[PDB]
Amino acid sequence: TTNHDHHIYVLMGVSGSGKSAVASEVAHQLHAAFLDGDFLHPRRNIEKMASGEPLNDDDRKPWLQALNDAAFAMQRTNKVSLIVCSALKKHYRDLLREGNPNLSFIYLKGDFDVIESRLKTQMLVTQFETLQEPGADETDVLVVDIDQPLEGVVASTIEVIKK
Amino acid sequence: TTNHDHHIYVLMGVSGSGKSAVASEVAHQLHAAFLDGDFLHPRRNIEKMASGEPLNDDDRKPWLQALNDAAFAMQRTNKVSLIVCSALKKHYRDLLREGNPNLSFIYLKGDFDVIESRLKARQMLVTQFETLQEPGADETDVLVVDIDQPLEGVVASTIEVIKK
Ligand SMILES: [Cl-]
Ligand SMILES: [Cl-]
Image (cartoon, rainbow over all chains, first blue to last red; front, side):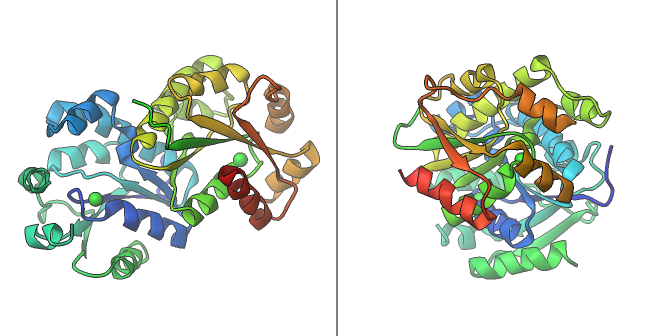
């Protein structure tokens, strides 16, 4: 039931890296399916998040699981699928990869100053702390330079789904 | 924690009535948020479908819960949220309504002739119209939109209805 011709792109990166804005535009340009993963967070996680707490590994497990099922669902009937999901850790990425050999990552990149100077500084401090940038041991990960205008980021995102 | 200034629109109707393609154009045209409900079925249902097995109320219960949750999550940070769900039974509509007084439906409506032919160009269909319970006078949060129009026409009509 995996359609190896079909593909899922997880747009990943810290909060404020413009993930949603990119995925939406790219998806309209490409007529792709699009799922903002924030929406799948379980009520508990949002309470915690909204209250001002940063989540941990076990808060995210059930969420990542939910993204995994939705990628599977989406690759059934869409040639190209986009999922916004921060996927900060390598272990989280692995959870998304399971049973999804046709799923890969677009890492919308930038460092602390760019992002901050793009915009709660603390939230942002903790994301970068949690971020584990994917090394040479993750073959299915492409990177986009977000130190550019939205339109250029979208286009680089496009040239990478089409490369 | 519902936010009454924000609103969720669920596009209902039988498969082939164009739900997803309409929602996308509207969502993009309105900088609105958009969730195609099909993507939230559990593995369970998706494996079943892969086996040409058409679902019953039970397969749908957890799917509909998941949707209800997404609706709520979506309305935290979006003035306008769009969700695609065929939602043919009244009981499913109420299942979406729970805790979401701020969610209504856009019933994308057309006779069988009109959807039949959209499908051929892409049995379940007859069955579908069969399962479809049309929302009566007692469902007050239901707007209807005629789909025997050019898609741009249908898109324009769904926006008209949301701005009402
Ligand atoms: Cl972001
Ligand atoms: Cl449809």
